[PDB]
Length: 459
View 1 (cartoon, rainbow, N blue to C red):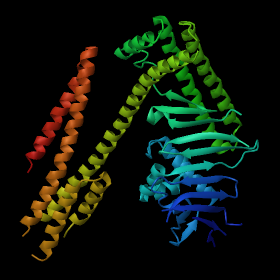
View 2: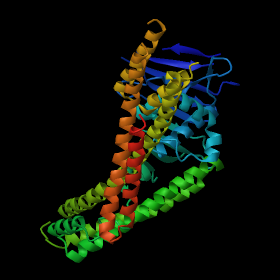
View 3: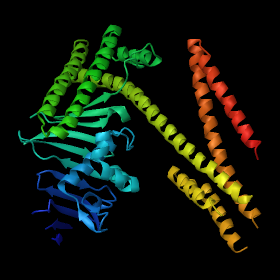
View 4: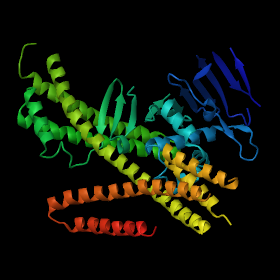
């Protein structure tokens, strides 16, 4: 049993099956700061935004499936919910690239996420979570932070203090914060606009020379930057690979090593910077600090173009994922409508329709907000409840209205998608000279039209 004592700061406590104790802080009375202390020596800290911690219970309690009773999460169960949240933080809040071992590990946290994602996404999105790990043999621990849904790793030894936040995969950019200076690292491929004979590289060259620099000095720096960035990115991803292994080993010597390896490259970037400041200093002779601010303006320019490309690449991938996800949902919705337009078509000429409409209703709700499909469903529900206590012509009308409404939206996206392919195909084919792929898209669009003209002709 547990008890809360007030003296706004309250205290949660009870130890044996008693794994933790917390200190909840209040303001205008809403929770603003939870503070979990576990027997492990591991720590959890939650900090609410302007609106404060919503559902503080989420971080401390679970609903027992066998009893219905509220049960306190174990220091293990806590760590695991953080591990699960860390997963989502790394994979743009989606459950796609979930490994089989991760599917074993997260089963329960997957189970409840599946019931209601809100609790998880709201937490991840709105609150400031900080988890400190159980101190390893060498007296070190790892703080795993979550801000604007953004993960941040930081190793603490109980001095060159280094923290790294961001997703290269999903944001296109990530950051290295070290004792204090911040470094932007971009996930751009080898053949990027900054590396190519682009209008962008053209202008980048024009602006670097104009700020007191030789064309061969500017172009050297561009490649030095792109080279530095790429090295940093690898070293960054390396710290993550260490952290991921550490998760199971329980040791931070490898993460310590990865930080040192990363630090090497961070100093390399420092050397690259001062060199520009020098090759700028020995150029006007009136003073040092003007050559520093002028160096900063130059790097800003490069980082600006690097950010624009990396995020645009990242945006396009994330969008591609949404357009696929929606297409899949609609394909599912189309199946549920194909079956309900058979179950009702057999009833019209005992009832089977009740479950197919029950499946379709769920399929539509799964997609998201469409208040005209909710209105179209209540119209069917109203016309159905009015046949029990009366014409069936008012029943078939609301059916065909709902059937037509969803089928038109389904057709509009399926055509949009196909044409967007053709657009790309045509754009690529007239650049490489091979229209063999545009022929494919066309023959598919023809076949889709025939399929849809035949389905219009079967009314």
